[PDB]
Image (cartoon, rainbow, N blue to C red; front, side):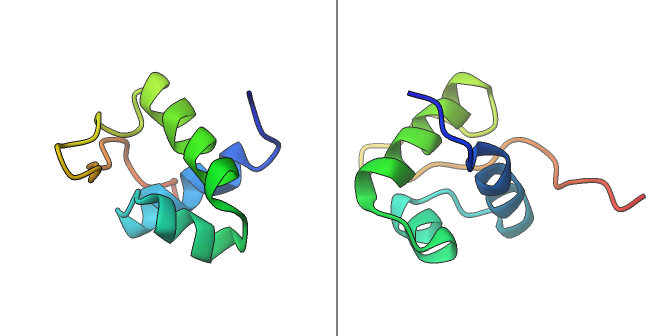
Length: 67
């Protein structure tokens, strides 16, 4: 269930290198379910790793280009 804010979430996670649901919630001022669905979309796209046993993920993709 795809979201218009996906690209903005990917800019945040690849700039910040944080991909927790709480970090995305705080940045975009959105709810848990909506943030969680975008992070699962990022995992399908190879932007972030699967979650570890504690739900933490690592950001794989590079930050946005500056030119």
